[PDB]
Image (cartoon, helix red, strand yellow):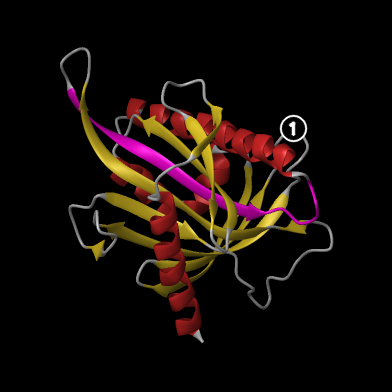
Amino acid sequence: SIDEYKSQANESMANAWRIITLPNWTVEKRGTVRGDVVESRKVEGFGKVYRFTGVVNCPARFLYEEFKNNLTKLPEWNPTILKCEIIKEIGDGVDLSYQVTAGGGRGIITPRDFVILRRTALLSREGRVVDDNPHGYIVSGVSVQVPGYPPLKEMVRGHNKVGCWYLQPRTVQTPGGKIEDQALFQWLMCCDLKGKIPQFVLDVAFATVMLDYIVHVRKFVAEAKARAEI
């Protein structure tokens, strides 16, 4: 039934918004760009969740549209994304997707495929879905079993317990006096790694996988600004 999936995605978006806005994180790794940090925390009945925080020089809305509507275009500008299909679109910004990723953590996170149920909504500062003027833009994700899209014997089927892109609009003033649209880019990740790989190893790998990803996001943004798309 469709509604079993609609409920799973709304529940997943709320879990993600609530988690990503929780206080008191543990800094795992810092990034090259001032402000970039991958933090972590223990979350009841999830485990050790991870969060990248960083500032992106583009309207939050624009990044939101790219994730929502151009998911299949991700492999073109992000080499860590091998494949991106939209399996089904099921209403209220909800959809199923099949994603294939490449290796990370210099050999720890092997190439994995994913069956993702997403929720796409504009959230208020209270976490209610609004139609305009939002505190942030959410693109949630959670792994689901979809018949016809089973695990391949030749690839690890990864499991996203909870995740999201949480993008907050930020109009800043530049050194040259100009007023411009920017975005607070937050990324939640709770990927269960099958087997018993000791936690200190995973902390380095997940943090690396995240900091590596943001290099391409900024390349996508810089190019989009040059083609005056933003």
Q: Position of residue 154 (x, y in %)?
A: 83, 58
Q: Nearer the viewer, residue 84 or 146?
A: 146
The magenta span reads 179-197
Q: Is 124 situated left or right of 52 in this image?
A: left
Residue name at image x 26 percent, y 41 percent: 169
Which residue is denoted by mark 1 in the rendering? 106
**Direction top: furthest residue:** 176
Report whether residue 79 is seen: no
Q: Please determine whether, in this image, residue 160 is positioned above or below residue 104.
A: below
Picture quadrant where residue 149 is located: bottom right
Q: Is residue 85 magenta?
A: no
Q: Position of residue 55 (x, y in %)?
A: 37, 31
**Direction right: furthest residue:** 153
Q: Amino acid at mark 1?
A: Arg
Q: Nearer the viewer, residue 117 or 53?
A: 53
Q: Please determine whether, in this image, residue 47 is positioned above or below residue 77.
A: below
Would you say the magenta stretch is mainly helix, strand or loop?
A: strand
Q: Is residue 190 magenta?
A: yes
Picture quadrant where residue 144 is located: bottom right
Q: Position of residue 94 (x, y in %)?
A: 42, 69
**Direction bottom: furthest residue:** 1
